[PDB]
Amino acid sequence: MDIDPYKEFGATVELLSFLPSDFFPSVRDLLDTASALYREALESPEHCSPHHTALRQAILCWGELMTLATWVGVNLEDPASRDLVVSYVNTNMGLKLRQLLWFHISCLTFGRETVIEYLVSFGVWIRTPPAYRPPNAPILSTLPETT
Amino acid sequence: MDIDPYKEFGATVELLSFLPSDFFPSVRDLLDTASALYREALESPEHCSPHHTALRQAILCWGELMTLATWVGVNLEDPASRDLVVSYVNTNMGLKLRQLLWFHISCLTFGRETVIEYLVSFGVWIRTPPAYRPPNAPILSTLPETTVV
Amino acid sequence: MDIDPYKEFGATVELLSFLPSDFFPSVRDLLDTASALYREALESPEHCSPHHTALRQAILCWGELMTLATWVGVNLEDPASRDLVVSYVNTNMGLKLRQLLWFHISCLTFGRETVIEYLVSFGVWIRTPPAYRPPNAPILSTLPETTVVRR
Amino acid sequence: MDIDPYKEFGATVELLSFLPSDFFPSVRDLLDTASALYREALESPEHCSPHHTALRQAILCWGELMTLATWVGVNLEDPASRDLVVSYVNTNMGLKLRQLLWFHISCLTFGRETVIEYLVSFGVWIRTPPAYRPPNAPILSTLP
């Protein structure tokens, strides 16, 4: 019924596609980041933030797609069809999860607005000609500047 | 990460296992009900509650599987290998999502503590052997079966 | 009527004429920037500011030139002809749009006073011969020169 | 994206579609009216109203198409392809600026709201079957 997953949080699908698709880290680096930082809270019987609620659902959505990739690997007899189904899940469906996991993990770590301004800032930077922009790409950091 | 989806909301996967697998209505009837009632909140840019956030994720999860089910139909030329995947998505992967839509649609309606007491009460009814089991099961309602106005 | 696009906004064609062609992002990058940022304000039934009014007209102006560039591809037989027409639209006419889109997008994000002060200081830098000027052009950006968003 | 040009001002493309294409005056007649009445304001270094801003943009859009049409004449040797492009700009592309020039010149002259009821009133007239249709169409007039 035309739902935007980011609209609830103050973003859009268009705003996350304003960053290159290859910018977002892999699926496993994001799952290991959520499991390192957030695992105790994700497994809690508490809502915590709406980011936790959304992030719990995305991790479970991906687990069912990995069960699908496993199911395809065994059941389907011909390798030609197995590989087109597994490659679609890991790349095409993976990209939309990579954006969604990156978004909520970043909004938990760095704050939600910080991620929204970063996401506008980085996208303008990548479209600015190199001579007229700051030389180094934007990045998010929790490490305070020594002063 | 285990991540029981129901644990956040006061239930478990084992608590929703009191319901048979064939208890849950079709995904189509559940999406119709979410649209008929909750659409304008689900398209809304607020956090209305955690159930809304969970539906918004479950409805987009199902939308991606239908994009998959449509993508596989075009891009798999081998019919036998195509019909197995299109089925597995509509039936096997549908069941868990069809159980998850039922839960959050039932909690927005009827209240959440009523759905948890329904699962307990329905479990007593379904565990009862058929000889001793009453003819009418527990059911979620805001009104008695006969409404005189 | 001799009308200056920039003069109601506090600039001129001459003030923006010092920016080189390679300064501006492409048309696609500027359209996507206005869309990713200002789309709901650009599509709202309100006057948000004169920069919004001016973007709405520039965006639809480019939409007509792309309808032209598509019409030329379909209805012109001569391949040498359809190439000179499509290139003139994308290169020469698009360059004037890139300048116009960049200006209003920048004045929405940084404010018009900041953009005008940037254009004054950029001209001093660009008019200086290369030997006598700092090797890096002035930068107009939201980032504190080190990036590293923090907060 | 979408960007209805008229929705900012209280109209739409659906509402200006009540007017036929051949209703609108020529670009020349519209530019002569803007130059007569509005030129000192259009060339002013200030925002008079959003209709001035939008009308400045449309006059500059038409000027770039006339630079195009002048350019296409010189730099296209094949006359068969040359006149197709020139006749497309002066006719097909000019038609949509005719609508946009007409709309803002009318809202500066007669008022924004007056042009909105004129579009409604002209639609009632143009939809009336010919037998019952009054012989004179609605027209914008500042005479009280």
Image (cartoon, coloured by chain):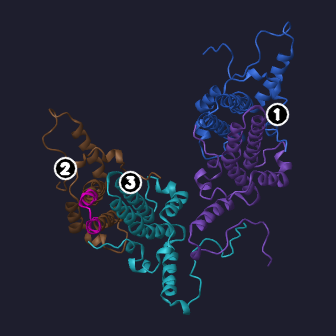
Chain colours: A purple, B blue, C cyan, D brown
Amino acid type, callout 2: Ile
Is label 3 on the same chain as label 1? no
Which mark is nearer the camera, 3 or 1? 3
Q: Which residue is mark 3?
A: C70
Q: Which residue is mark 1?
A: B11
Pointer 1 local density, CA inside 10 Å: few below 14, some 14–19, many at least 20:
some
Expressed as whole percent of the image width and height from the top left, the position of residue B50 reads: 72, 41
Q: Which residue is mark 2?
A: D139
Left or right: A138 in relation to D39:
right
The alpha-carbon separation of the residues under discs 2 and 3 comes to 37 Å
Pointer 2 local density, CA inside 10 Å: few below 14, some 14–19, many at least 20:
few
Amino acid type, callout 3: Thr
**Subunit of label 2:** D
Is label 2 on the same chain as label 3? no
Q: Secondary structure at mark 2?
A: loop
Q: Secondary structure at mark 1?
A: loop
Locate the N terminus of chain B by quadrant.
Answer: top right
